[PDB]
Length: 48
Length: 48
Image (cartoon, rainbow over all chains, first blue to last red):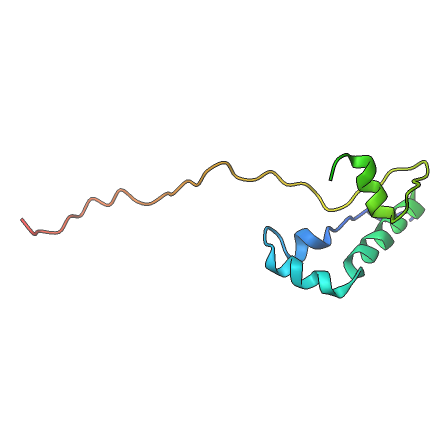
């Protein structure tokens, strides 16, 4: 094997899909899900 | 909140964006109306 599947997970659509309160609550956690998505994009580009 | 270039500027937290491609949370289409579906129940109450 050479490469894996290029998964991309949207943190907001996953945790607080179609809602405002949970997104406003998660906004207090900083950049966790955003940096996880950035790491996933890095995984994808390194697979490429 | 004006153009996607400024959106990428907010994303990278810098006034200068290099040659590349980025974005943020996905844009979702909202439902136009609400459709209620319920049976056509035939049994009536014999109040008559």
